[PDB]
Image (cartoon, rainbow, N blue to C red):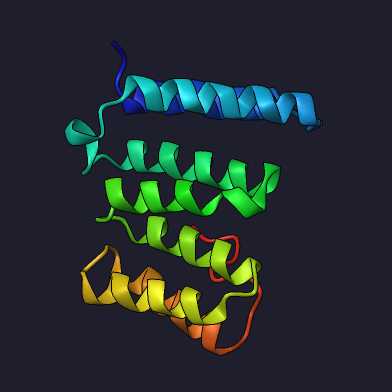
Length: 141
């Protein structure tokens, strides 16, 4: 069975081929991400960055499709991929978008306390939250 890097490569190609986006194409994409998650045991991949990207994208797609039921998918991604700062920032971004500023800050502070990496990404996110910006992270690379 293919690993997370092979699955992510297929999933990103499907996202590129799902333009212009529609409800039907969004449902198809979410379905394909669920198939990757069903095929990838989290106990083998907790330290895998491509696996963290798969779990985060599923949660982000669910936040578009049904924001009132997306929290559990961010909690799953954080439970499985806690090492990566971008996982915690994605959850904090979701909370911020829902108007839960206090929860967004607590998620970022807990990630700093628990040593999610890289630290710099978390400091930028905390600065942007304190500056009252809508996005914790801009078009960053």
